[PDB]
Amino acid sequence: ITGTSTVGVGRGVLGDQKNINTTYSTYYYLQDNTRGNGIFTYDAKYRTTLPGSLWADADNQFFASYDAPAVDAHYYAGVTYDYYKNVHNRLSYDGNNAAIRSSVHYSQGYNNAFWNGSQMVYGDGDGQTFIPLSGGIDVVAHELTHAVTDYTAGLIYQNESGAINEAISDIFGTLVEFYANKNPDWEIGEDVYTPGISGDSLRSMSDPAKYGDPDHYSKRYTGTQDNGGVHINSGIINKAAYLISQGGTHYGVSVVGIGRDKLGKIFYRALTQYLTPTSNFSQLRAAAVQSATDLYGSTSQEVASVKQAFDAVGVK
Ligand SMILES: CC(C)C[C@H](NC(=O)[C@@H](NP(=O)(O)CNC(=O)OCc1ccccc1)C(C)C)C(=O)O
Ligand SMILES: [Ca+2]
Ligand SMILES: [Ca+2]
Ligand SMILES: [Ca+2]
Ligand SMILES: [Ca+2]
Ligand SMILES: [Zn+2]
Image (cartoon, rainbow, N blue to C red; front, top):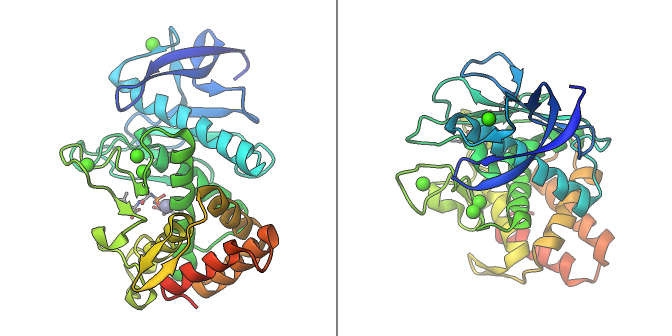
């Protein structure tokens, strides 16, 4: 919409107050003009036609319970934008500041979120398994990251390349959570998953087995569910990623941690310069080794740790 940039205030899904960038033109719209070619948040109004209506508000105050999911979708999209620009020098998901669009209140009781090829989509959850999913910064960065992947490596969404696609979104969803540095962890979706149960999450990168996901290649799922287990087999790469950053001894294999920042640089480089739509785990190991080599030299600790990590999850 054409208008003048403003700043609204409201409350997100977890009750936190935050400033949001809006645009004023009779109404205040959830349109942030301060980043790239804008960040736009839409109301799907509990239906499934997308994107729905650009979020319109009469007074630039977003404290209603109905406003909360939009507030967090809009704000965490901005945090994710900032991560890619400030940390990887990437402008929006396409690298050329494409407009970023999100819809909230999608469908009824919808226990998921996704990238539909053109925009992010967030259900409200059924209130038991989930609360509105945009309340999770890792979830928002996971989704936006699916866009980054689609514009870059293009990892096909099935079997091993699909588990890599998924791990990539969990890794950067996690790196963004640490970047915002509000209660960060190596867990996925803990802020919005099962309001009645403390301490659980969708997935764990540090111990995928905790929620039934493999942490070794010999435990990979090869059935047909979940597109060949893309949300299951991602645990093998997630673990490898957690190990590279934090170190550890896994099935007797010891890994010297190198830190999140180097983990993000190596995986960012693998994602945009070496992965292809059909890469498999073994090809991801080589991409990561070549990326660490590029950034830190073939004799660095970094390359050595990347090797240790893939050994540890049984990926050759
Ligand atoms: C929601 C969770 C219980 C499990 C899981 N979803 C997730 O882990 C994450 N959602 P996601 O983005 O991976 C769902 N992706 C997804 O459904 O992709 C299918 C698709 C949709 C539109 C166009 C092309 C392809 C998010 C919730 C962190 C799943 O879809 O299995
Ligand atoms: Ca209002
Ligand atoms: Ca957290
Ligand atoms: Ca998390
Ligand atoms: Ca919970
Ligand atoms: Zn995903």
